[PDB]
Image (tube, helix red, strand yellow):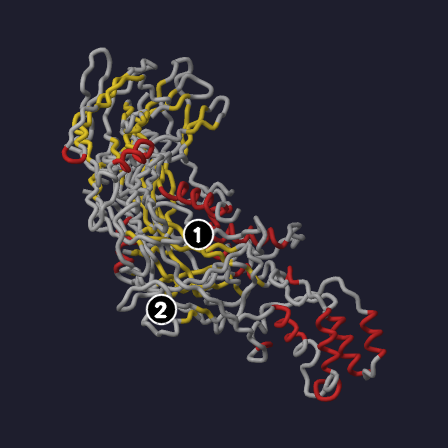
Amino acid sequence: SSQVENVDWIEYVMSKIRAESNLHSRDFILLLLDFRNSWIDGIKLNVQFEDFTSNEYHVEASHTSRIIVPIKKIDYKKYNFENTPIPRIYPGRQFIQSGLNEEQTIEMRQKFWCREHIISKLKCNWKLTTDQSVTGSVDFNKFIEKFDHKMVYTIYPGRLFYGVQLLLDEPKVKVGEIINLKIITEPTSTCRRKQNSTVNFLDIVIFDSKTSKILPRSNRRILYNGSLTKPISTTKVSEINLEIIPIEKGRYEFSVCISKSNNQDGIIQFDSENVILSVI
Amino acid sequence: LLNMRLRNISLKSEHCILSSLDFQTSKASEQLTKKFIYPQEHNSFLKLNFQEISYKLIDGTSQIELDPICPLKVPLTAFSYDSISATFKLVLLPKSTQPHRVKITLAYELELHPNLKLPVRTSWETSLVNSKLSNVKFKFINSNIKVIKGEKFTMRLQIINSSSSPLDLVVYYNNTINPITLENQYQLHNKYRKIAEGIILLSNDYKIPYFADLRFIGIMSGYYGTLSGLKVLDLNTNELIEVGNGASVLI
Amino acid sequence: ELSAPDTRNDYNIRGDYIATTPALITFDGNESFINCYEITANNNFDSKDIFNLKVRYNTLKEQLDCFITDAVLIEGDVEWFILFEKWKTFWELEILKKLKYDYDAFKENRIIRLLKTSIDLNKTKSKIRNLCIEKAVLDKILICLNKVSRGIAVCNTDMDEYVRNLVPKQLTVPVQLPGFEQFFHVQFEQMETSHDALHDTIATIGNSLSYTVIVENLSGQWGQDVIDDGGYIFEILSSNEWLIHGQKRCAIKEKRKEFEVHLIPLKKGYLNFPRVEITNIN
């Protein structure tokens, strides 16, 4: 909301959610990194990404200060992240066998290439306090040690099995409007993985805005015409749809969950779009 | 006995234990009396319950209730006035004398002298977490229910221990999903995906040396009662000490 | 489809289910199918009429067998012209003993037969006058369906208006209670804590007996509980009601009853005989 524009990293995603309204929210991520100085002087620490301008920080002699740098995601249908992997500085060499599984080679390629992507645009700049002349920079090549499986999910969305988006038209609904919900599903670059299951199952789950876990029989609540299983097609887009006749409460969230079969714990993606509607 | 009653005292750890005796003139004498009155052509009695107060101890003092008591006179009603009572520090159970009076103005304006005043024993019938390894105790100096928007806020934690090794604890908030019936299978995940996404601790790995002001900002809004991500730990003999206390509404 | 009654008495409906494209279900009842309908009110608010519904159901063993008799055996203008032309009653006697295993009809496969046999069926096909090409196509189809699988393709292509639709009907008739009234309460949060931020439930209940009770419960909260013991003055209108508590508690027990159905009868001025109380925080 407005008047929160007193904090340096808010106004970037505010200023591109006001203009360029195609570039929505809930996809901007924050990368969080802590400086620590092994020196007796203060450091002033203005960080630049490709357009983000952090304010005049200060780190005294041990006091860490976690910079909260906002970036966007990357699009898996825009870059190919399965290109020649770990390219050598100079061509040639022995050409020995890799000695690793092809699947391992895939995750090593992703965990390198996302790392250099966040290296390539991040430039710190700094100056000392007690001299105000000896400015400098750093580079983060020795700093960012590797990625793990949380990080490659959060930057790269193509590591997930499916990618959905889901819109509900006109979120001010009074009582009596049977209104279709629209789901657009698109399988990712890990459409090549399984392929012996040709159907996967999509539970649409219902949360209250304040409390949780609305039971699926759902009286005095959303009533649904159809059922909430709706099996979806691997390797093709599929527009599922369900109609919501609401009875009475304040606000709710919708989200989906994919489960690969209909047995217990075969579930694969706890996906989290969560659109909210407001009901009088 | 006509007006059936019960004594409900509820105990809270905010040093309060309220008392609200409930009264209801039940069917046992009603089935006889409202057929004598039905023969006398009456089915809306009015016993004027207007005079009632409690007693605390041998100093029989009328304690000030949290609710009011006007002239209450109707048919087949039931009432339960709530009274604030001070909670004792221990099991010193103050026996009480519940006093009340209803002047039974019957049919043809016939008043009858009656009262309900008797005595019994008013037993209730029943911040900090301690350590596991040291004498250390954790409390929050700032109040555990607090208001904020999505902006920044100051939060302050007590560490009081024994000064045999008074040092070397670390914090970290551990913003990752605990990886975990199908609706419970998406309920535990949606609990954990708002624990590990809601607030972020802006000075993690804070070396403590008593007092420390821990530094958070919250992203998304709700009721984060027992905000349970943050873990201090003793660097010798590593035990996962948790501080599952405090709350933050973000509206 | 839900049916308005034969009186045509202006009972409006808003929702209705026409699954034109999703001709697709599975009904082992562990998963739940729910259909809901939003009936509206007429100029007059009455109780009893007739309601019927056009459940146009089918059977899965008709659908996959109509796929198997049109794609996996007889998808040509030669075999269905001369090989299985007039011997279709033998195919419709062969089909109804197949017992296709439907536990994996909606788990990574479709049309995967269970453990029957085929040598006795081949002996029965040889003991009739079946030709060598027709026996070749039928043995090829049974050999393919000895172990097979399918995607969700031809979910309606192999039954595109080539199937019967056993349109059932029933009779639901809008059951109603005994006593109709309308209350309106008045809440006042005289809270022992600060506020629990409770979430609302503006109830609207019914009661069907005589000399009866129509109880109610307050809102449910989720903060530090057993508190926010509210204050309430009743202010019930257009009736001669009863009471349970003045300035009650919103604790683990609430018990805010109103035994108003022992007196004050009225008419059936609504769709049923109800009472819609509504508190307000003042």
Residue A124, given in percent of the width and then of the height, sits at 34, 45
Q: Is residue C106 left or right of residue B201?
A: right
Specify whether residue A280 is in view: yes
Name the amino acid, label 1. Answer: Ile
Tag 1's secondary structure?
A: loop
Of all residues, the one furthest to the top in this rendering is B58
Specify whether residue A172 is in view: no
**In this view, A194 is above or below A132:** below
Residue C24, given in percent of the width and then of the height, sits at 54, 68
Q: Is residue C109 left or right of residue C171?
A: right
Residue B145, given in percent of the width and then of the height, sits at 28, 33
Between residue C217 and residue C192, name the one nearer to us: C217
Residue C13 disc label: 2
Q: Is the C-beta separation of discs 2 and 1 under 8 Å?
A: no
Label 1 neighbourhood size at 10 Å, few (<14), some (14-19), many (20+)?
many
- Quarter that holds the N terminus of chain C: bottom left
Q: CA distance from mark 2 to mark 1?
A: 48 Å
Q: Chain of mark 2?
A: C
**In this view, C194 is above or below A27:** above
Q: Is residue A64 left or right of residue A4?
A: right
Q: Are marks 2 and 1 on the same chain?
A: no
Label 2 neighbourhood size at 10 Å, few (<14), some (14-19), many (20+)?
some
Tally the numbered discs: 2
Residue C115 image-quadrant placement: bottom right
Report which residue position mark 1 lands on: A155
Residue B47 image-quadrant placement: top left
Tag 2's secondary structure?
A: loop
Name the amino acid, label 2. Answer: Ile
Q: Is residue C33 left or right of residue A193?
A: left
